[PDB]
């Protein structure tokens, strides 16, 4: 019932792994909040392990299209989509708590079926992978080359380390 | 069992 | 339950298993899916028949669902390595990997029974393998290599071009004995020897 | 969960999961009820879906066509199978897609069981459905039936831009 | 538990298994469902009896639920290939695939016991196979071939027209020994050889 | 664990299993439920004892829960086929299928031990078979045939009318040794040879 | 909550396989609707795989006993009871969507127990089978011989094919 | 369950189970909402907990420190792992404990998986977290980092009195 | 099912297993994943062939998915300990641990069949091991030693620098027969000996 | 699959298993976790080699994860009891219990292969044992006895003080061959005997 | 089963 | 299957 | 595989 | 492993 | 174990 109190404050909370169910509700909430008042900012509090990309990008698109600025706060942890959506926030309004930890890494899929089917699955992996690194490079301001290099293996950032890398603009004292 | 089986 | 029979000569008496009698006649029997176990057993058998009489032909009877790729190429290389010619006979089916082994016999000595069937399709993965895109990118790369390699090997034994095989193997292609003969997988179809 | 109720007031229905009979029944009902309130105003269908059963999907499609009002379709996260079909089934010119939305189109997937006689019948229907799906997808996209059948053989993915070209959606949303 | 017995002659002593004694007499026993395991064993046994005495008849005792199609045609081809005539005897039942093997014996040498039964039905798939319509279209095509092939093979051995077989096999058809004789699946029905009777 | 014993004669030494010694005496032991496995083994044993000495009687010791119908008729036909007379002896019970096999011994040679029991009932299906009514109509038709066929077989061996068998087998009927003798399933009851 | 809005419109929806639970509710709804107004028609929307006959006929009987006409709409699919209840609608008020598919086939039971018990179960199979074919013949207007023949194996009908065979009167 | 709503009116939030993301988010929200209503009044956190994940735990900790109002911490049944940390993280002088409450302090517990390369990375973080936890626990208790690390090597239990002396809590409740 | 064959000489008759015939010819067969069971058996076999004829080469046929580290180094040390040279032959694949054993053969005597493949990757842990940071710190320390040790071992046998090995093994690297030869894992690739 | 080989002399032919040949050479192989089964088998083997030639050294090859405490002390006592000296060799690892057995060999005869490793840790209980505090008080007491008893045995064989062992075993300590030699668990590290090298 | 099988 | 295999 | 292994 | 074990 | 068992 507390989440309802937050919604009145124009705060939406991503507290779990990103999936279609959470994404749909989140997209809706953003549209509804933008419908009520398009001037006021929307704040997204993020504590998440990460989740599916398709659902994650559904959230991302809705953020961009929203008239108002979207402020992102990293509470406990931001990983995968958690990190992506965090960095996707309106520049200067991206926040992180002191002990918040950010994780950035390469995408994780799976392959199955005939060699013909797998070849297609591999094609898409290349499409997604390139697009993720492209946008992450834009958010952080790092070269696409470094994002790809750093993302090869899990790379953890503290609030300070994340601040320097360009994931978040401010740390909250 | 003889007688007679067997 | 498989019965054992008995043979006798002036030199002595011999109790033997039906499959042993076949191996005495230089007949290796592949009756099961191809795996590391089955492959190792077949390779061992081939090298033995090689050792005993390298000049005499070796016979491979094939009834199989098919099986693993590495296991198939293990058997394939051994077949081609051995100095002796290799005759392949298909009973009731040869599918996927087994279809390649059937075709991998030495030219002219590849045959099948009339009601046998032959299945050819591209390599498939039934389960799901997961990991980072970098790992999957490598697996997918290998999988395409294994596909193309199956296509090339089938191509030279059947005589068809690799491009033709690739088109035919895109979907499962079932072939009767005669249809398999025309495709170039087998040279002849055995006819019943019964008198009546 | 209360947000879906708020959307309904805005004449927005949301398909957020795989298409099944349960969801289809609810979606069809909502469309009829919305058309009853006001038949002039458009209805918006937001689509993020993996796809689902054809039979359940066509119950939705039929209801869309019969509705007096226009049906606008938005591809949010993903549109696949019935997701792609219903997306393209939207009123022409009112079909929208988000920038990173992905559309999947492919051949139908059934299963066969029972006696050779029963399977023979199941195969007959497969031919019927397959033709009908390709026909309508050809009509929605404006592509020839031959290309739909050819492209649908294996999974074919479209980006927002690629989908825009193929005729699945008319607009991309800025 | 299966007991082993002992035989003796001036040449030596022999301890043997009942199934070995049957095979010594050129009797192959099919007691189980037809599968790759059972099929390979029967083919091996047939080819052996071929090697030892190709001029002497081979006998097949059949009590079976039936089994796989590829496995059936493997045995069938081997039966027909072998130079020796093949006698088939049905004990207690021969069903589906097994009924074909029963009928596949050489003419006049196909027989059954009086209370044995024979089942004939079209090929069926108990489970479900899934995939794209392109794949199912191919499987369904093959399935029809296997159906028709069972009908043609049954037709020439029974003497019935393939069309009649197709009609009768649409649903499960159970036949007694005598009914199987009339159908043309077996030539004769064995009579009790007992002395007291 | 079953111990093996040892026998010796001027011709040599023989180590043998108790069940082998029984079979050496022309005794087939059915100790288990009747199934495709058990049926095939018994048929093999019968045909062997036929081969060795077709003129000498064969003995069947029966302790069984019963079993499948096809498996029963497989054993039954083989019993009736063999030239040698067949003696049947029941130990501790013969139920369902086994009761028929007990009664199927040649007349006068069917017997049982005093505390043994005999169960007779109509064929039953524990599980469920499903399908179109056309299929069930055929299955149900066959099932009735098998029922009547068990009734016919019991009838000629017991001497009772098929109608009586049908009436008695509608429900499970348990018979003592003496009760089975009166019913016509066995000819005699073995008596203790002790003091 | 939409079903409540439909009930106000005198629309009841059969969206799943027919069982006792749904049947009781459907029968109840029909009786209550007929109690409020016996003049106004009741509409039954059908998307169903089919289900048990006994539960299905409870619905059918209630439809017939109702004073008001019962209009039947085939939405996604009508199979087994779905097809039966669809065709059982008031003649001329039976409707179908364009891509709705109708499946008609022979009944499917099961047997268990003693041969005596199975004999009884088989008796009932013949009883039900005749009654189903009779009513299906009445609805479609086809001869019982053709109903029995066509129902032997699964027979699928499109909306157009269903219209000709006599399952539904109109296509929307 | 209706009592927690009644406690919230008294500005009392209750941590009654192991610390996870679900509970942490709810607790953080409540703290922010309570501070929004009135930033002058203290917030009381009643703690009976076995402990839980660090990430979720630190989210709570940060929210405490950033809050304008003081956070009073009460150890009711048990304080272990994060329970002990959050207990000691309370405003100095406003940290309370019941007489029979028991406090457990120990080294962090992680896990490692994957390739040797991945494990090397996982191990890097272990060193980072461990130092920080010991640093703050040393700050809360007022003990040297050297003694915290030594005592934290194995599970170390404190009674209310022992915890009072060690510096976890300022008062015991009579 | 593996058939047994029969050999005869003036001295007597011998019934033997194909795998026994291979061992009679000084051929050890590693056909399975490397584990404590398989390792102990191979070490035993190695020491026997050492005992019988220490001056004659020992042959190792390898088709394996790979396996445990301790099991690998157990076999490795035993291979290197034995006085006799060791020939390694790869059939159908040698992966992970097995790839190291393949390379551990004595120089010049390492070979593979044409369609065989070789997989190399860094050591991995499929499950999860849990405990206090102090314990994980120790496990992690050992794991790095094992990683570096595999790199060093591969380095001296292949001839590549340890740094190169570390880079290539970060991700799974599949090698064909020829690719394995160039990498330095095997010395030569066997060519088909067939007469026809 | 483990192949059997064949040896021949003027006296006859001998077909034997590799492990039999090792035992013929007085080599006991511990390849598995230490348990009552493995312990009983090893004790039997030790007492046999005692019986046959008590004056000749016995060899123990050790590759083991370790195992139960009682099972270990069963093997340990038997090793020390036997009149013959015992050589211990470690292949690929000796862990926990096995490390003690490795160290329990007679001085100078304890060795390992170069890439073998050795694990030492205090006794641990993987599962959970429940009961009244009185029962747990006893279990906890016994566990401490077994810990301390492991420390004393390791102490006298390695030469280290019991207190040092306790300190080192508090956390798992992995040792390479050379590190195990320095610790005093083994006397020497085997060097490769190869001719080509 | 002889005569005649075998 | 001789002739000719084998 | 001789020559040369073995 | 001789010398010296055994 | 001798002496004395056995
Ligand atoms: C738990 C991981 C999750 C399953 C996966 N997402 C994932 O791995 O996201 C990580 C990420 C990295 C960079 C930027 C954003 C996100 C995913 O959506 N995979 C898709 C990939 C597909 C869209 C190609 C899938 O296979 O379902
Ligand atoms: C894309 C499928 C792949 C070729 C293989 N599947 C596979 O062997 O499928 C059967 C098959 C079909 C046609 C021809 C040969 C074999 C597999 O994954 N097995 C691999 C292991 C895997 C890690 C690639 C193996 O057997 O080594
Ligand atoms: C998960 C797939 C699903 C089961 C299947 N649908 C399906 O495969 O839809 C794919 C599609 C293609 C083109 C346009 C729209 C959708 C289906 O409805 N199959 C039916 C059979 C069909 C002949 C109606 C069923 O088996 O239930
Ligand atoms: C339509 C059923 C098909 C003929 C077969 N089923 C099958 O063999 O059913 C038993 C049977 C009945 C009558 C006569 C012969 C056999 C099957 O699917 N088995 C195949 C595999 C499948 C991929 C076709 C096999 O055993 O090879
Ligand atoms: C109505 C029951 C039927 C006779 C049989 N059950 C069956 O054998 O029940 C035991 C039994 C009781 C009395 C006498 C004989 C046997 C069965 O279904 N078994 C059949 C298979 C089934 C498809 C008819 C078999 O074993 O062949
Ligand atoms: C899944 C099918 C379902 C179980 C079956 N119904 C069923 O198969 O209905 C099909 C149908 C066909 C034509 C006309 C009406 C209906 C049924 O209720 N059978 C009854 C039969 C019994 C009343 C004799 C039952 O076994 O419960
Ligand atoms: C109760 C076990 C729990 C899994 C673990 N927490 C944990 O062990 O917290 C104990 C603690 C120690 C010192 C000070 C405060 C608390 C944890 O979060 N571990 C993290 C470690 C990671 C942040 C490096 C994880 O592996 O998920
Ligand atoms: C980091 C993984 C580790 C090297 C090992 N995994 C392992 O052996 O992975 C297979 C492997 C790959 C490449 C080279 C050699 C082996 C493992 O954990 N097995 C250990 C036990 C573990 C406690 C270290 C063993 O088998 O002894
Ligand atoms: C505290 C652990 C205890 C020493 C033992 N565990 C145990 O044997 O762990 C392995 C081990 C480690 C180091 C040294 C020797 C062995 C156990 O509970 N096993 C006992 C039974 C138990 C009731 C004490 C046994 O095997 O006798
Ligand atoms: C009845 O007395 C049976 C005796 C068995 C004997 C003939 C052979 C063990
Ligand atoms: C038919 O009488 C069969 C008899 C089997 C016999 C020839 C060998 C056991
Ligand atoms: C083909 O006729 C095969 C016969 C097998 C025979 C040579 C040995 C059992
Ligand atoms: C390579 O040709 C190996 C042959 C094996 C042979 C020496 C013994 C079976
Ligand atoms: C060390 O070299 C051990 C060798 C074993 C040998 C004495 C007997 C197989
Ligand atoms: C005690 O030393 C026991 C020794 C066993 C020996 C007598 C026989 C293996």
Image (tube, coloured by chain):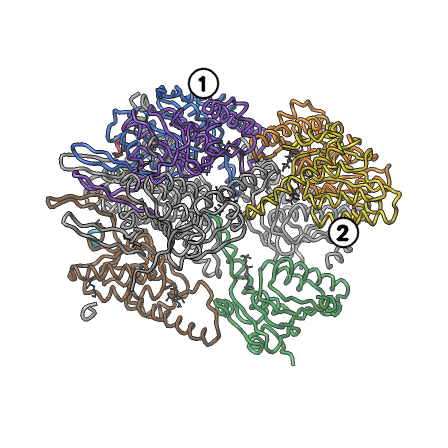
Chain colours: C blue, D orange, E purple, G yellow, H green, J brown, M red, N cyan
Q: Nearer the viewer, residue C190 or M1?
A: C190
Q: Quadrant of residue J135?
A: bottom left
Q: Position of residue H30 (x, y in %)?
A: 71, 62
**Residue drawn where x is 17% and y is 44% of the image:** J7
Q: Nearer the viewer, residue J147 or H72?
A: J147
Callout 2: residue from which chain? D
Asked if residue G42 lies left or right of residue J156, the reply is right
- Specify whether tag 2 is near ligand 1 (CB below 8 Å): no
Q: Quadrant of residue D66?
A: top right
Q: Is residue G47 visible?
A: yes
Q: Is residue H144 above or below residue D89?
A: below
Q: Position of residue D91 (x, y in %)?
A: 78, 32
Q: Nearer the viewer, residue E118 or J139?
A: E118
Q: Is residue H102 above or below residue E184?
A: below
Point out which mark residue D2 bears.
2
Q: Is residue E93 above or below residue H139?
A: above
**Residue drawn where x is 41% and y is 29% of the image:** E188
Q: Position of residue D118 (x, y in %)?
A: 59, 32
Asked if residue J157 lies left or right of residue G88, the reply is left
* Mark count: 2
Q: Which residue is mark 1?
A: C182
Q: Nearer the viewer, residue E107 or H39?
A: E107
Q: CA distance from mark 2 to mark 1?
A: 67 Å
Asked if residue J9 lies left or right of residue H32, the reply is left
Q: Quadrant of the C terminus of chain D?
A: top right
Dot 2: few (<14), some (14–19), or many (≥20) neighbours within 10 Å?
few
**Residue drawn where x is 45% and y is 24% of the image:** E157
Dot 1: few (<14), some (14–19), or many (≥20) neighbours within 10 Å?
some
Label 1 SS? helix
Label 2 SS? loop
């Amino acid at each position: 019932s507390v989440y309802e109190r937050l919604l009145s404050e124009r705060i939406i909370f991503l507290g779990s792994e990103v999936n279609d169910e959470i994404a749909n509700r989140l997209c809706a909430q953003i549209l509804l909040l933008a419908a009520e008042d398009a001037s006021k900012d929307i704040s997204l509090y993020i504590n998440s392990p990460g989740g599916s990309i398709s659902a994650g990008m559904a959230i991302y698109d809705t953020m961009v299209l929203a008239p108002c600025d979207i402020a992102t706060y990293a509470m406990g942890m931001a990983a995968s989509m958690g990190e992506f959506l965090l960095a996707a926030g309106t520049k200067g309004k991206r926040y992180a708590l002191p002990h918040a930890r950010i994780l950035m890494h390469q995408p994780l899929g799976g392959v199955t079926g005939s060699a013909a089917d797998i070849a297609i699955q591999a094609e898409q992996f290349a499409v997604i992978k390139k697009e993720m690194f492209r946008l992450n490079a834009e958010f952080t301001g790092q070269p696409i080359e470094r994002i790809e290099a750093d993302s090869d293996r899990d790379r953890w950032f503290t609030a300070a380390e994340a601040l320097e890398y360009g994931f978040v603009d401010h740390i909250i004292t | 069992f003889t007688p007679x089986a067997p | 339950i498989l019965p054992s029979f008995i043979e006798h000569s002036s030199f002595g008496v011999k109790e033997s298993n039906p499959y042993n009698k076949l191996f005495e006649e230089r007949i290796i029997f592949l009756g099961v899916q191809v795996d590391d176990a089955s492959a190792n057993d077949i390779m061992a058998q081939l090298l033995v028949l090689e050792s005993l009489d390298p000049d005499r032909d070796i016979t491979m009877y094939i009834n199989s669902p098919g099986g693993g790729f590495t296991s198939l190429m293990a058997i394939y290389d051994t077949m081609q390595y051995v100095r002796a010619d290799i005759q392949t006979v298909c009973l009731g089916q040869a599918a996927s990997a087994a279809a390649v082994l059937l075709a991998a016999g030495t030219p002219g000595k590849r045959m099948a029974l009339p009601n046998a069937r032959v299945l050819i399709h591209q390599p498939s993965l039934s389960g799901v393998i997961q990991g980072q895109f970098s790992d999957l990118e490598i697996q997918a790369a290998e999988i395409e290599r294994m596909r193309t390699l199956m296509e090339t090997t089938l191509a030279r034994h059947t005589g068809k071009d690799a491009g033709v095989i690739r088109k035919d193997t895109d979907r499962d292609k079932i072939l009767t004995a005669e249809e398999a003969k025309d495709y170039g997988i087998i040279d002849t179809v055995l006819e019943y020897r019964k008198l009546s």
